[PDB]
Amino acid sequence: SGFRKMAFPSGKVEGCMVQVTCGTTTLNGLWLDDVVYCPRHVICTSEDMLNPNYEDLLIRKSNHNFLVQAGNVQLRVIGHSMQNCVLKLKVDTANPKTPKYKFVRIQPGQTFSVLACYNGSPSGVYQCAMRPNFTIKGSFLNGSCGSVGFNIDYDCVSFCYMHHMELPTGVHAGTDLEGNFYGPFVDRQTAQAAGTDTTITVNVLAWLYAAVINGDRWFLNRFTTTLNDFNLVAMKYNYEPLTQDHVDILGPLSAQTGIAVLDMCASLKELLQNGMNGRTILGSALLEDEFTPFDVVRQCSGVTF
Amino acid sequence: SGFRKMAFPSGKVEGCMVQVTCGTTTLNGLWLDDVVYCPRHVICTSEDMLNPNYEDLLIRKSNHNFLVQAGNVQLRVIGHSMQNCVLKLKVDTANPKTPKYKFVRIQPGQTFSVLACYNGSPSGVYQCAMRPNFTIKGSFLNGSCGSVGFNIDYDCVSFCYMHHMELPTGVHAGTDLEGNFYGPFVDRQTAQAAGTDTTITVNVLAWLYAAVINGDRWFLNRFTTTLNDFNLVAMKYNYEPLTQDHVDILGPLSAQTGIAVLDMCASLKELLQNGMNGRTILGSALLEDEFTPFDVVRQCSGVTFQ
Ligand SMILES: CN(C)c1ccc(N(Cc2cccc(Cl)c2)C(=O)Cc2cncc3ccccc23)nc1
Ligand SMILES: CN(C)c1ccc(N(Cc2cccc(Cl)c2)C(=O)Cc2cncc3ccccc23)nc1
Ligand SMILES: [Cl-]
Image 1 (tube, rainbow over the protein chains, first blue to last red):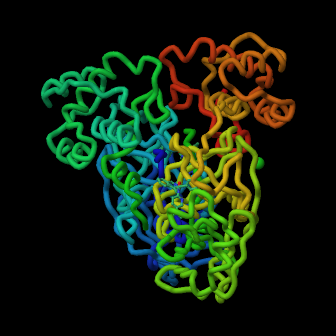
Image 2 (image 1 turned 45 degrees about the vertical axis):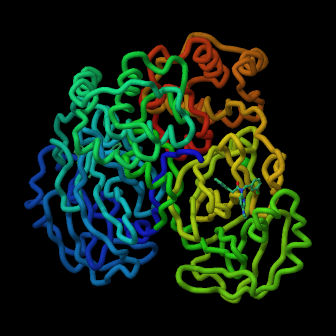
Image 3 (image 1 turned 180 degrees about the vertical axis):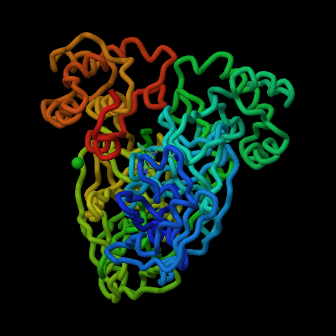
């Protein structure tokens, strides 16, 4: 019993974290095989960030300008290239701790673990979701750039996020490991803002199923609804639309608890319209949307890596 | 910016997790140097659990009755001894991945990361706190016994908890790494129950300072309180008494934000009286008590967003 915001074990990723220094800028790099991946803004000074021409800034650098440190060992950079907003530093040594891995681009609503790092040293691990507005509500200070997000499936680490920046509202923005930003953000010190966010409906429903599996059932009711009526209500409270794909994905949880997805949608409609009336669900007075249906099944079944 | 329930990176502990089997029972063990630590109830059957005589059960075992698996490698048990509620299995191989470590017994209110494991394989990592009633609100299924709690301040792993059981309310009980239980619990399936739990006041105050550091002050007020009047109010909402030690510990956070400890206590008194009125604090509609003053200093910026 119990239900916690659980991250994947971070060991396979910790063995890939390195410190990348270029001039006065120090940040984190991800060392996989013979390449170190890091944000391309490592080559910028504070003035450069105002309007950087990364190709022009990069052509002025030699391999020896990039200092890469793995633990207390200096790696030697033997090549460099840029792919979108990520800099790839070819090193002479393949990382002996390289796990089985893939680079995956995730969709909003999907969750992942973040291994927050400073100076190439892991500091903490936490779970978060890619918001519908493509930001992440992370916990990052200056120097955390290059920290990564990942998921694990079997023995394979799927890297999905690399940290680049903090927006004015305190939320965060970054790229996939191919350097493509999530959201309409750019790596330049210019006016940028997170758009209005919405709640991840399928994830709230998954968490309601998790509450039922854990004995919290006060919100259940005799009612059901239709997908169309539910979507009208959900749109009113800034909730993401629920699709037939989402209902299909919630099938296993619906079968285990005996509560149909539209039966749970009727519970969610009532909670949106009336609140919790002083009650809590899994220790929360807010409807939690950072657990996916897969996260709920995984935590409630004890899947290991 | 941001404030998350953050766990320590688990890699140093993952490299120590092993599977321990004794007969039909399989659980997790912690392999440090040439010793594997695990709950002594690994030698029990389901029937043995009501009134087990561990000394009598253990004397009937030989080293080769304990099967220890580290990855796909069988370790050889060359000795065994019981220390309180932990079994220590001496093995013929020192763990090459043994980090710098210490065993520490923690006090209620202290937080730690839990690396939940099944069959010697890590499943997830989350942050926990030792409740004032000595239980932990973990996430553990059957087979999670032997999973450990730890902190990793400055590259040294301080092991503070080993999981033993789940109480009827769905909360968890365990021991320190010397096998001493936290709380009035025993490793017997006799009628046991968690005592009435209370809120960790010093931690709620730490989290209110975290909210001020991150730029939010909506909950503050122009009032102060004496320590005694605060405690008289706090106890009415099932909050733990705040001691002078707690006031001293909050000193650094008070100095960084410019808000006196007893002034933050007056804000807490008002929050308890009024609720949040549709507002949130650091993304929460409840007063959070699983962040210590030390956790807030570690995670938050050293510069307040004034
Ligand atoms: C030195 N230099 C290379 C540098 C300096 C500052 C930054 N910026 C500004 C910025 C603004 C538009 C776009 C981008 Cl990509 C970057 C960041 O946002 C980094 C950052 C990341 N996470 C948490 C943070 C908390 C406080 C301050 C900064 C944080 N990036 C590079
Ligand atoms: C056979 N075997 C060794 C065994 C069997 C059962 C158990 N007990 C019962 C028990 C009750 C009083 C005290 C203790 Cl120490 C043990 C447990 O509580 C194990 C346990 C731990 N965590 C989460 C759980 C979730 C569901 C079911 C069990 C869980 N322990 C050992
Ligand atoms: Cl302590």
